Image 1 (cartoon, rainbow, N blue to C red):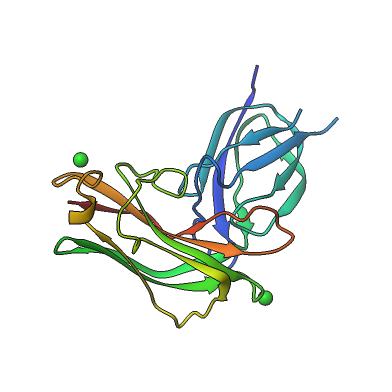
Image 2 (image 1 turned 180 degrees about the horizontal axis):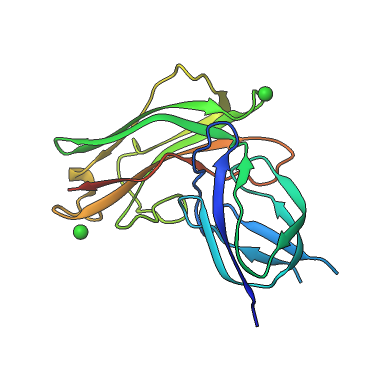
Length: 210
Ligand SMILES: [Cl-]
Ligand SMILES: [Cl-]
């Protein structure tokens, strides 16, 4: 049986902050044992944990995520516990994120920073859910259209620009119920080439009691 365990974090190479995604249909650790390819899944915060791994040498691969792809060759998993943080370049960084309730409206304000100059902006969205696993993969269907904006053609990222997204609670009382706790998460979807399928970048989850 398995003789090892491994845990660690997906970290921004520049800021050292956790890089969040969606556990399902988001970032993933693809590994190949030396000598059939398995996947190690990552919680939404960017922290990962696996208590069922075999002590061996691997090739690690990152693809179709929300950060620039790369490989880690000759990755040794020792017998027992192992710790390893991966340093990445997200396509987009959400800056100064703020999510607050004013009256009967949830308002998100933020700025964006490109991971590389070539990165453009395709979408922005204020995701909402009844639990902390909120994201593009775990979300409520909302009315009004102000919770999401699509840029076609994809637009330039300028750090000085202030973006605003809104959710009207009265127009969404069916899924955002009065007196209950909800988790809101700012997401930004980049437009990038050679990197396969681009996934959303996120700001940390904000819990609000309605
Ligand atoms: Cl650059
Ligand atoms: Cl609740």
